[PDB]
Image (tube, rainbow, N blue to C red):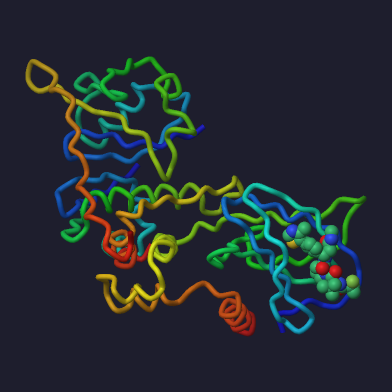
Amino acid sequence: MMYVKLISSDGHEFIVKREHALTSGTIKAMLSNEVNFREIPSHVLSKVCMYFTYKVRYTNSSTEIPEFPIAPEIALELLMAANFLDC
Amino acid sequence: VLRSVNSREPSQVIFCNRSPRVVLPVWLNFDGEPQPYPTLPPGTGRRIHSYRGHLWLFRDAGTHDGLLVNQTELFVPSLNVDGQPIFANITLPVYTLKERCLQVVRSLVKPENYRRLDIVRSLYEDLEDHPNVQKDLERLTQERIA
Amino acid sequence: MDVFLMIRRHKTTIFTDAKESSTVFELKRIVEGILKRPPDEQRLYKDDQLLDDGKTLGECGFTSQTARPQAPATVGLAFRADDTFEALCIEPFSSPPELPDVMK
Ligand SMILES: CNC(=O)C[C@H](NC(=O)[C@@H]1C[C@@H](O)CN1C(=O)[C@@H](NC(=O)C1(F)CC1)C(C)(C)C)c1ccc(-c2scnc2C)cc1
């Protein structure tokens, strides 16, 4: 089982499955095993990783999909991160 | 082009809202013009009378976000078997993170204030580009041709 | 059933899934392959409580309702350092900025 490390601007290290990380087109182009995001804080990058899990779990599934939650306080930076990550 | 066919052949359907959104069923009339039908609260189902060859799409009733019906965009009522109505299972798509983020930001900011956000020029154009059944019908029609 | 987790120690966070029937020991084997520390040098926690190896994740409170893909449950991790186990320490994520004027 392969894993990749995504590091936030504040140095938090997020270890996610390689398959999940390849959800982001930007990340997939850099890997196809450690990426540093000097602009993405941990309160945003932790949510990016939750989205990878949510996407892999519910894509091509007929079990009722729940809403992906986003607190008002992270919405703007998560929008900036998502636009750069292409996910 | 994308319109309901006037078959006059009855078809019993169940609009089943398996999503957390208030759903707006939209029927494409015989001219291709979208026609709104009564909303469906989250987690509810309605037995409706439709016809074979009719076209339907489902949206979030307040924001117009695109929803899925039987894993696709359009639902077309068909012939029933032994009194079985046709289920139209309406679900949330797995939206992109970007689109999900645009939805949340549109729900918190008044449209006159989008340009007052501290973001790149491109993200203003994405925010301003509200979900629209007419624009989506244009996209579907173009994608059907090629 | 699948359960979705965040295994957290200091400034490290592992995102992983496991079965509700799977054990605390099997989660340690997952941590071993990533952080290169054997299960005997690891302590797993649910809040401040040390979890036992033979217990299932479901028995530890990790269920489809609490450990979701979009809101995973937190498992605390502490390594052994020389003679003693270090105290459980989880660095919090950064503080989001104050809501803009137009977003209130
Ligand atoms: C039970 N009554 C009906 O189904 C009735 C109604 N059903 C309709 O209005 C159906 C929907 C669509 O298939 C066109 N249509 C018609 O009946 C059309 N008639 C015909 O094509 C002909 F009769 C053959 C000539 C008409 C719009 C021109 C009148 C309806 C449908 C859905 C709802 C909804 S959508 C969300 N909640 C509910 C309950 C409500 C009413």
Report the residue at 35% width, 22% height from top.
C24
Q: Is residue B30 above or below residue B69?
A: below
On the picture, is B103 further left or further right than A62? left
Q: Is residue C5 above or below residue A13?
A: above
Image spot of residue A49 (x, y percent): 33, 49
Write the residue at 63% across / 84% down: B145
Residue B9 location, quadrant = bottom right
Q: Residue at x 59, y 51 (%)?
A: B19
Specify the quarter for ligand 1. bottom right
**Residue farthest toward the left in the current orientation of the protein:** C82
Tell me which corner region of the image, top left, top right, bottom left or bottom right, holds residue C89: top left
Q: Would you say B69 lies left or right of B52 here?
A: left
- Position of A62 with respect to A50 (left or right) is right
Residue B142 visible in image: yes
Q: Position of residue C41 (x, y in %)?
A: 19, 21
Q: Pick the residue in front: A61 or B17.
A: B17
Q: Position of residue A75 (x, y in %)?
A: 34, 58
Classify residue B99 as left or right of residue A6: right
Q: Does B118 sit above or below residue A21? A: below
Tally the numbered discs: 0
Along the line of sight, the residue nearer the viewer: B72 or B42: B42
Quick check: can you spot residue A32? no
Q: Classify the position of the C terminus of chain C by image quarter.
A: bottom left
Which residue is at the front of the view, C58 or C27?
A: C58
Residue A8, x across and y down, in percent: 19, 52
